[PDB]
Image (spheres, coloured by chain):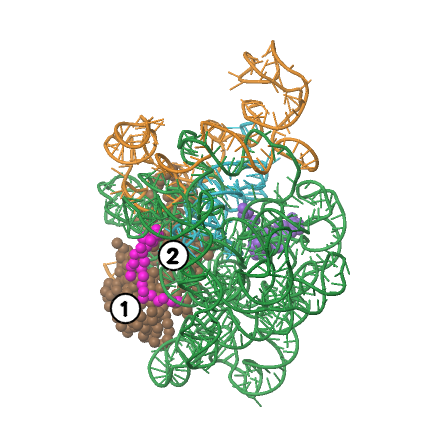
Chain colours: A purple, B brown, C orange, D green, E cyan
Amino acid sequence: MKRTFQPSVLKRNRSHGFRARMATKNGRQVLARRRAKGRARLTVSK
Amino acid sequence: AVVKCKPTSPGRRHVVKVVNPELHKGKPFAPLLEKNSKSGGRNNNGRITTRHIGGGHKQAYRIVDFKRNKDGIPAVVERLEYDPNRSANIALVLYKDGERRYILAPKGLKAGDQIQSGVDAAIKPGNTLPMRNIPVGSTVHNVEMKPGKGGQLARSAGTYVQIVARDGAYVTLRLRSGEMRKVEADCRATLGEVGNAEHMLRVLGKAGAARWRGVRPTVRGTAMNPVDHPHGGGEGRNFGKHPVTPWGVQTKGKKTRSNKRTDKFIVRRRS
RNA sequence: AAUUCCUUGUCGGGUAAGUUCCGACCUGCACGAAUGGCGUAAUGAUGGCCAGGCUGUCUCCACCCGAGACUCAGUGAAAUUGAACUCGCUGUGAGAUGCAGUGUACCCGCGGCAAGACGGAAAGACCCCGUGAACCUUUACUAUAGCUUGACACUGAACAU
RNA sequence: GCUCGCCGGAAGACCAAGGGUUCCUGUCCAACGUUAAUCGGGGCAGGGUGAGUCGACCCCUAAGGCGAGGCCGAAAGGCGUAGUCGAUGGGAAACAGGUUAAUAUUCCUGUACUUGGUGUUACUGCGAAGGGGGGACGGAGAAGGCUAUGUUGGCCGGGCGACGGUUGUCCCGGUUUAAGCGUGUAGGCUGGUUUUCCAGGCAAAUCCGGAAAAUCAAGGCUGAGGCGUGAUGACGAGGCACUACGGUGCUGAAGCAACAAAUGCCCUGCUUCCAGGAAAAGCCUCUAAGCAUCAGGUAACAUCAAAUCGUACCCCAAACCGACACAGGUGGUCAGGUAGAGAAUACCAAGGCGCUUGAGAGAACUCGGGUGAAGGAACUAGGCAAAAUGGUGCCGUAACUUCGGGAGAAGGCACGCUGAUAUGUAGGUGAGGUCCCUCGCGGAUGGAGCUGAAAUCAGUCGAAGAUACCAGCUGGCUGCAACUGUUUAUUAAAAACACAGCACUGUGCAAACACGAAAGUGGACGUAUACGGUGUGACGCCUGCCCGGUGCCGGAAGGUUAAUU
RNA sequence: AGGACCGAACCGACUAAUGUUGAAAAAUUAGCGGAUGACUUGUGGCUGGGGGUGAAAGGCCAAUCAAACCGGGAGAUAGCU
């Protein structure tokens, strides 16, 4: 049975990568919220 | 020519084909070709703006000359070609100076016939002249609506318009729809009728034939649920309301023309 | 009749016997002509019905080959669980292992069966209730996008009546 | 280690995606492994991934994203031009052998190739963000010529048989060799060459396109494979000195032919059809602005450079997605033998495995199967399930029909093996020899050798010859839908949804309509034989009556009627 | 020639049994349908919540759909347990 998660590094970065988050105001707010929370891993870049 | 396919299997019993042997059996003129990417009926927002559009065979656009501004240059027809972007056929014309262009095919234009555009051009099918010079009552096609804009009327498979009267700067025309419209006499027009009369006689014969054209299936609307269409659902087949479009418009006689911008060039709507 | 309530309508065919099926009849509860009517070859993992072949489907089960079940060694769950020294019957309190009377019964496992413990599982979905929701409908109410009408503004010039 | 069993269009081999050390060696057995564990994809330590040619990066672009200005929008922001990004596509070059416990087209040996920089020499019109060519493109079908590959023979080496025979028509194994370079064949495409002229290719042009003459027919391009060379080499069954029986030096025979043959190659070809089949760059040419005893361009030689990153291992699975060492899911490539139409199926080769609890017993009952007296649907809501039919060839085949079908209708007969026809035929393949020549990978004749059906006749074995696996039950009446398709992922596959066809209606293009506060976009680079919406639903015969209601489309006399005044 | 025929791969999911604290939060086994097309598949892209998409089932939109998910208004309100 095919499951929901079909990994793809290229699609992973384009959808949730660091540059993608910086591309929009709302995405930049996501990083700001995560930085305020002190997240060790800001995004899924690596 | 119209030929009926033999009923060797379902899906071919009712297939009627329009075979034209005169059409070129080869690749078109590459220089006058352009990329034509499909849209699926979706605009720049990505939303379906026109339904029932999608799929179909890949097509390459042909640069058809709808202006015919090469005044005073005799041209000779090289061959007739099949155009996937339009119902009518197109003809490859070679001008006396070595330039090749694509034009709509009139009723009786073949390889070797000569055509010419301009005020002094002869009154023969395929020739383009301003409607001021064209005698009243003759049948024309590819009519221009504005001076120099390019042909915009009677471009279909076998359509044509006729000049009914010359009142001065404007010429009244009887369009295929029956509309009596007037345009400036300076507008250009092509003599004759676009020749594909048999185009309306074809029978697709099967569902797949429509899909080849890029026409996706149409869901009626009475077969949907109320959340989807005004015709909605019901237990069985009820349909107890006035017919409407999606989004709630009568679409059973209700006139939707509200332009009012020109509303002066129109003499009689139709019928 | 995918439509017929009365109804298994009536007659005929098929069967020893046919509420189904097929063919007619018309008394169409409550068919009907593009929310189509009546036909229709072909097609269908489609509905109904009848035959030949075929058989453990059955009369009526028998034997056999394997995997479990069973025993030994190793590892090692689960739902459930107020507490239990946790029997039958009749009666009682509204269908009793637990009350009354009476009968029966040495203590404890293992393999089986599933009648009861109103067995386990899911704060019944049916039903009603709440001045509870949610979507949906419309000639319910009140609004509103859109469409449409006119006035004024953007907006002037002469001429004639 | 010897047997046995299982897969073998994989349960083998090589990758992408993804994972990220699971790879190799040593060591340890608490935990992890559904048991034990000396073992492990477990713990610990060490080791391991070598590139001008593979891939990425890089050059080029598709869908699409972003977007200087710009247009639009309360703000946020939206769309989009010039541009710039974006592979799943296009663009230069490496093959064979050997080698490590673990890497190799990356290292080593041998033999090659590509694109650039600099310099020398000779000959020289060079030059672009421009022009043209090219790149460059569909589906189906059809053969023909080939190769991969396989079979047999020949050759070489070895063998003479645990039990009758086996020195022969016997048995086992091997018989392998690339890129590159040269040759330019089967076959495909195209008529060349020279001069003159021209409203075209945003300006120019010797290039492209077009026009008019002259002159010859042989010019050119593309092109699998074969052959030669690469190769006096490498590899090589097996031997000989070493030989911790763990393995290395040296040596190492034959290394040919015939036939069959692909879904691969010629083929981005050919034929044919309608639904009419990417873009851009590299590359080849054209000149402009400009530079000209320069600079640049062409060829040869020499020299230098080709960086950086990935490279282990798994990759139909115990390493990826499923919480698991989970009967699930996961794209590409490779495609042996016998039988067979076949990538089905059976049995096997190479290779890989026996699926991480076993040992006994041989109860009920459950699960998966085999067989069955007599009867044969009496079962049951229902022939559910099971049983049965099953192949090829020939004969034969109804109603009905849209004349295609129905149809493999139904039904019947023959199938093994041996021999002969014919010591292996018809057919296919085709050597030597002879003849011809513009003598060449040539043509004709020629038929050796090899390969090889099918049929007839006769004989013969069994209960049974399409013997296994594999492999249609058939027929009659009838409802519904024409049909192929589509649908409730995870209880509904249907008579529902689509459908071709039909009709009504809207829409004259800045179209109707749709998404958008707007710009704008789709509709459409379309134009009434078009497009949107609605209903109906192939086809055949037809589709009657009613406009009071509601809606829609017109109408003008009057009545009523908003802001405003 | 064919939304032609028989039939593997491939894509489907009609019947039955098993399983139902399953090997599996939909699978296995034996049959079954399509299998040159309205086919199927890899990679990437686009459409966003009263919205998308939908050969239409209220289907699907990350095991969730008559209005997804996450955070917030928020300790919504609960004449009810």
Q: In the picture, residue B118 is in which quadrant?
A: bottom left
Examine the structure image and report whether residue B211 is included in the region drawn in magenta: no
- The crowd level at tag 1 (other Cα within 10 Å; few <14, some 14-19, many 20+) is many
Q: Which residue shows up at 24% across the image and 65% down it?
A: B138
Which numbered circle lies on residue B125? 1
Q: Which residue shows up at 33% across the image and 56% down it?
A: B260
Amino acid type, label 2: Arg
Q: Chain of mark 2?
A: B
Q: Position of residue B69 (x, y in %)?
A: 34, 71
- The crowd level at tag 2 (other Cα within 10 Å; few <14, some 14-19, many 20+) is some
Q: Helix, strand or loop at disc 2?
A: loop
The correct choice, above or below, for D328 with respect to D118 in the image is above
Q: Position of residue D128 (x, y in %)?
A: 52, 75
Residues drawn in magenta: B1-27
The correct choice, above or below, for A16 with respect to D51 in the image is above
Amino acid type, label 1: Pro
**What is the magenta segment's predominant secondary structure?**
loop
Of residue C125 and residue C57, the one placed in the foreground of this image is C57
Q: Position of residue D520 (x, y in %)?
A: 44, 59
Q: Which residue is mark 2?
A: B213
Asked whether the residues under marks 1 and 2 belong to the same chain, the reply is yes
Mark closer to the chain start, 1 or 2: 1
Q: Is label 1 or label 2 in front?
A: 2
Q: Chain of mark 1?
A: B
Check contact, mark 1 vs mark 2: CB within 8 A: no
